[PDB]
Image 1: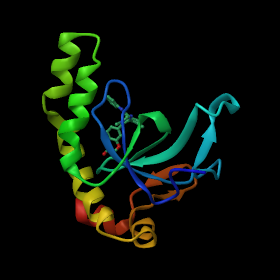
Image 2: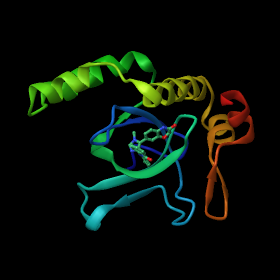
Image 3: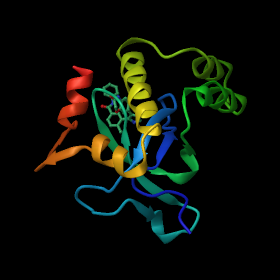
Image 4: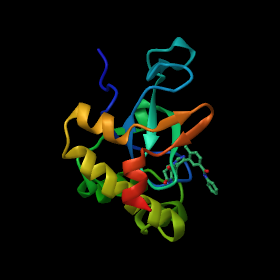
Length: 148
Ligand SMILES: Cc1ccc(C(=O)Nc2ccccc2)cc1-c1ncn(C)c1-c1ccc2c(c1)OCC(=O)N2
């Protein structure tokens, strides 16, 4: 019984990065969207797209995913992440807001993710799925137009 499917929106937590808005999707080369790392039931991964103007994709462990509703969740995510931060500087980094080009990308991503959330599964899959030209990842022409 899978928690997510292609088109579902999630927040992803990767070490060294803030919680990021994402959408579960199929890996363009592997053609799967979920896997068991080492065939262990506890190490399930999902393939996700990271929302923003500079797109990326990755296999993220399900344990590092929280279903996405909106930016309102973000404050509590940082708080829960800082609660178990093994350092005070590590807790300061998590509670402090995002800066630089990363902030710009994160806000762009929140704008696309909240639009995707207001859409149905098939509408958001048709609009936000990355277009792949051989080995190049491109943003959907419409999404690229709305970003820049
Ligand atoms: C999966 C990935 C691939 C490559 C890179 C990468 O290139 N990182 C890097 C770090 C320092 C200097 C230069 C490059 C980061 C991630 C990455 N891991 C976790 N998160 C949250 C991301 C990520 C961060 C920002 C955006 C993003 C994804 O996608 C949409 C977008 O506009 N911004």
